[PDB]
Image 1 (cartoon, each protein chain N blue to C red):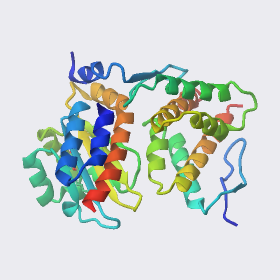
Image 2: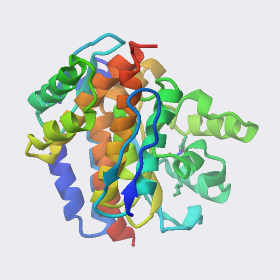
Image 3: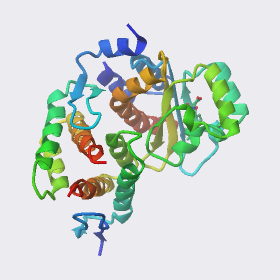
Image 4: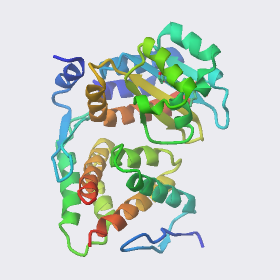
Length: 82
Length: 94
Length: 166
Ligand SMILES: CCCCCCCCCC(=O)CC(=O)N[C@H]1CCOC1=O
């Protein structure tokens, strides 16, 4: 039901999380933020996109959802150095 | 003694370093409290996962690593370091 | 020193002491000018937001009447992004912006940055600091080093500033 989904990307791609409360919008927010950083090549720090991005979520549960999606997204392209 | 350098000189102690990796690295960062160890825990934590093979559990290393630090201020030092390390190797890879 | 300023920020009783602490902290961080602006959720009445700081008086007066809030590249950035925006010449593209820039530059607001604010109760705002450095290289290097401390300032300021503006 209140499942959340991190869309597949390049390498190791996907997920099946039962999140404690509804949080798909927060997951997307985290994916988009990370790919917006990967895409637009380093013009600001990656830490900055993570920290300022997380701030914009209201709740600990949302913030944490943001983080999971952000780090997963990085994982995907990081692995992609096959 | 420039202006911007004079601000660095006080705050001597509160400065912390994220050593260079591959890409244009050595970040020098001012922190509200001394936090070099938290910084290094985040650097090592991130290398440990990289120096691992067919790798696939990134959030876990981050979640378990941050959780081992007891103050908000160290947690964020660890996050900044760990992520900077995942940056150093995202640009040293085209 | 900075940790103490954070606590004083949260302990603040009224707009006056808080805005005083905010300036005293900017000055300690080597930033001679700071502005904090914050609107309630879903408002664009820029000139009637909670706005504090020590921006040059002549300039603030001009900014309000001219309605520069709708010109300022940093203001529209704040409403569309989370990432901080350095004041690179490049953020000023259009004519009215190349012109907003000339005058802002005369007011002393040359080098600096704007951090967008997105409060928990959907509040919107901007935290800007300006630094007097020898050139842009020195300034951007400087601001990247202190950016983590500034992001924490942003955080204590947004949290304590919302329950005083509102
Ligand atoms: C999201 C804005 C809502 C609150 C309204 C704030 C209006 C003032 C914003 C401002 O002063 C930002 C600022 O620092 N602009 C800089 C850019 C160049 O010099 C300026 O004055």
